[PDB]
Amino acid sequence: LRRLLVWTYDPKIRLKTLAALVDHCQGRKGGELASAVHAYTKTGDPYMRSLVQHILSLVSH
Amino acid sequence: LIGKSINFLHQVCHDQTPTTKTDLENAFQGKIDAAYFETSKYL
Amino acid sequence: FEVLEKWIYRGIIHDPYSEFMVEEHELRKERIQEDYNDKYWDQRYTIVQQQIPSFLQKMADKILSTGKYLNVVRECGHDVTCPVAKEIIYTLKERAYVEQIEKAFNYASKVLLDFLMEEKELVAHLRSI
Image 1 (cartoon, rainbow over the protein chains, first blue to last red):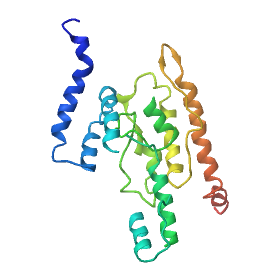
Image 2: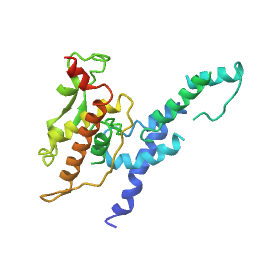
Image 3: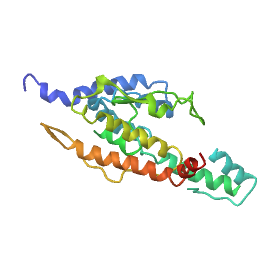
Image 4: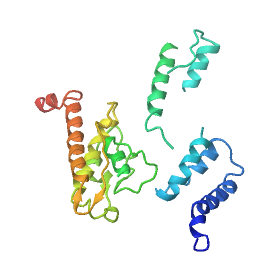
């Protein structure tokens, strides 16, 4: 599918972002980790903000 | 301050009350002030 | 427009980023429990030119004045919220936005003016002058 572009588009960002977030939140637990994932909702950024905000809602539960 | 006032109210001053009454879009400033009012007033 | 409606219906911005055409200068550490600048009506709540989309430029003064009025009732303890909210979209040479901006404007000024003329009475302050 154009050499698998449109297959890849939805998990591509979710793989980069979660692979970033696992090594950014190492050494951090609780409220400090909850802030370190709410760190990503800051240029507005509707494409990234739609992605992170569901995960953060469970993370800060 | 709410947790402090209610724990002083329990362990010393008795007449205990449990259950003193991403975003929630202003549910913090509503829950916390009401709880704070009730606990410190009863103390 | 959801960030807009957050700024419009209550004075607090419920977006935890600042992308919006209104920005809030932090002059909270100069004037607090006294006014010596009138910071609200000068430039604390100001607009920024490069965040104007160039279809809200006709509404810009109204948009600013709306939430500027909301802050000074949402701060002192009066419960204010949306009376009603409806979706607005950029549509080609037609406006959903104008009809909500006008109703928002009248709601802003009405709640501020009603709350002031009863508590912290302007009537007696002008009479005793």
